[PDB]
């Protein structure tokens, strides 16, 4: 399509380069955004229920990709 | 087209990958908008 | 993990990073002779359209008769409304 | 008596659930793993 219209296919390669680099931060940024919510919230559950302490440690274990 | 053929291998790969990341990035937003209805519609259904 | 290096995309980065690239296809036109005006209109998307109907051209080639090409015998006459 | 306020609290948390997914999605910590601040994307500090 870029060739048909006489566009800049090389710029698209740069566009893809900026596309992958920026959106790699999206997947990681979202993951890190929602991973810290996982780590901190699980730590909060650990500080409210004493009788179910061991279970909360399992939530973090199963929340990882082992 | 031929002189560009050197990049014929790693352009579609990123085009799909970027859309896949965009899909999940936006599907979550489209996902979230659904819950707002569910947070009221589902409560009504229950 | 660095996906750029994992999938062997670093070489592409070193070749297509921030540099001077023409917004048009004027990086290959100058090598060719004659004055070429960039035909980037909608009517030039035929080649895209040509691929949805391969059957327009049969398997190998269309019928050809070299003898019938005698119409290419051209006189010596001028040509208005046309510049070289 | 007290269960009436329990339902209000339960519904109050339900409203807060959709608000959580409405904040941690378009925002996020600006990690340097992909130097996203250089270009088109927006900005939201941690």
Image (cartoon, coloured by chain):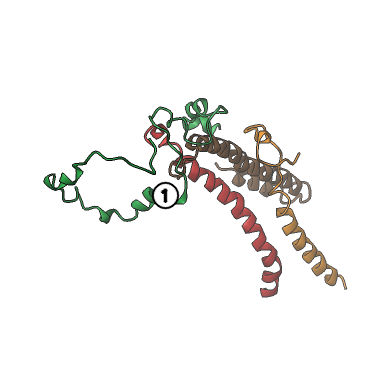
- Residue plotted at (47% across, 35% down): C25
Q: Is residue B40 above or below residue C32?
A: below
Is any part of residue C23 visible from this angle?
Answer: yes
The hue in which chain D appears in the rendered picture of the protein: orange
Q: Is residue A33 left or right of residue C37?
A: right
The residue wearing badge 1 is C45
- Residue B44 drawn at (x, y percent): 70, 74
Shade representing chain B: red
Residue found at the very far left of the displayed protein: C67
Residue in the foreground of this view, choosing between D13 and C40: C40
For label 1, the SS is helix
Quadrant into which the N terminus of chain A falls: top left
Residue C19 percent location from the top left of the image: 56, 27
Residues D6 and A5: in front is A5
- Residue displayed at 60% across by 46% down: A62
Q: Chain letter for green?
A: C
User: At 53% from the left edge and 38% from the top edge, which residue is drawn?
Assistant: A16
- Quadrant into which the C terminus of chain A falls: top right
Q: Report crowding for label 1: few under 14, some 14 to 19, many 20 or more residues within 10 A (C-alpha).
A: some
Give the answer, above or below, for where C2 lies relative to C59: above
As drawn, the chain in brown is A
């Amino acid at each position: 399509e870029y060739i048909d219209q006489g566009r800049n296919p090389q710029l698209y390669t740069k566009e893809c380069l900026e596309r992958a680099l920026a959106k790699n931060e999206q997947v990681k940024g979202k993951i890190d955004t929602m991973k810290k919510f996982k780590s901190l919230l699980i730590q909060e559950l650990s500080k409210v229920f004493p009788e179910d302490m061991a279970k909360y440690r399992s939530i973090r274990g199963e929340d990882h990709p082992p | 087209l031929v002189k560009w053929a050197n990049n014929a291998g790693k352009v579609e790969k990123c085009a799909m990958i970027s859309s896949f990341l965009d899909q999940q990035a936006i599907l979550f937003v489209d996902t979230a908008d659904r819950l707002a209805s569910l947070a009221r519609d589902a409560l009504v259904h229950a | 993990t660095n996906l750029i290096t994992h999938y062997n995309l670093e070489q592409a980065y070193n070749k297509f990073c921030g540099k001077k690239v023409k917004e048009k296809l004027s990086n290959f036109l100058p090598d060719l002779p004659g004055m070429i005006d960039l035909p980037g209109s909608h009517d030039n998307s035929s080649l895209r359209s040509l691929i949805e109907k391969p059957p327009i051209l049969s398997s190998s080639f269309n019928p050809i008769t070299g003898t019938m090409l005698a119409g290419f015998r051209l006189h010596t006459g001028p040509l208005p409304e046309q510049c070289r | 008596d007290r269960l009436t306020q329990l339902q209000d609290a339960v519904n109050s948390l339900a409203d807060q659930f959709c608000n959580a997914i409405g904040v941690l999605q378009q925002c996020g910590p600006p990690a340097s793993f992909n130097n996203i601040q250089t270009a088109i994307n927006k900005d939201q500090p941690a």
